[PDB]
């Protein structure tokens, strides 16, 4: 790979990371995080604005070109028998399927399923 190739990938924060260590990154859910170094499985190094620092690798999600990122606006319980999922308000998800019957397939990074478009706001 070319040096710094990690930086060409689009990632968004899934969680609030409040910096405590001197070299910790600090970010909020939905922010774009540039990944600088992913060599270590425990902590990645990334950049947001004017800080380069360490952060948890599973606190960010990859967004491929054309992909849509949403913030859940209302907690909703889906019918699991027809591939629906339950999400809480304020969760961050990536859309993975075209809208059908007022539902879109979304990914939290831990789970995937259909969720209502009425309860999502694009970020």
Image: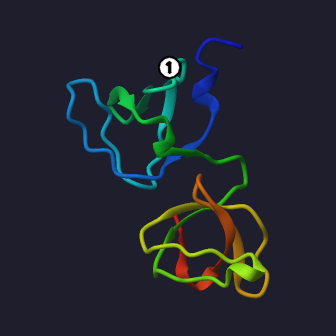
Name the colour scheme: rainbow
Residue at screen point 52% across, 83% down: 76
| Rendered location of residue 113, percent (x, y) | 69, 69
| Residue 103 sits above or below residue 26 on the image | below
Is 7 situated left or right of 17 in this image? Answer: right
State the residue position of label 1.
40
Name the one closer to the observer, 19 or 4: 19
**Helix, strand or loop at disc 1?**
loop
Residue at screen point 42% across, 36% down: 56
Q: Note whether residue 23 is visible.
A: yes
| Residue 100 sits above or below residue 58 on the image | below
Label 1 neighbourhood size at 10 Å, few (<14), some (14-19), many (20+)? few
Residue at screen point 58% across, 85% down: 118
| Rendered location of residue 105, percent (x, y) | 72, 69
| Rendered location of residue 31, percent (x, y) | 44, 50
Is 77 situated left or right of 28 in this image? Answer: right
Quadrant of res 50:
top left
Residue at screen point 67% across, 85% down: 79
């Amino acid at each position: 790979s070319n040096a710094g190739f990690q930086q060409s990938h689009y990632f968004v924060a899934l969680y609030r990371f409040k910096a405590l260590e001197k070299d910790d990154l600090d970010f909020r859910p939905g922010e774009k995080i540039t990944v600088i170094d992913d060599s270590n499985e425990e902590w990645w190094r990334g950049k947001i604005g004017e800080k380069v620092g360490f952060f948890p690798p599973n606190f960010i999600i990859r967004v491929r070109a054309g992909e849509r990122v949403h913030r859940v606006t209302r907690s909703f319980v889906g019918n699991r028998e027809i591939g629906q999922i339950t999400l809480n308000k304020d969760q961050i998800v990536v859309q993975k399927g075209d809208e059908a019957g007022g539902y879109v397939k979304v990914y939290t990074g831990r789970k995937v399923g259909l969720f209502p478009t009425d309860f999502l706001e694009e970020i």
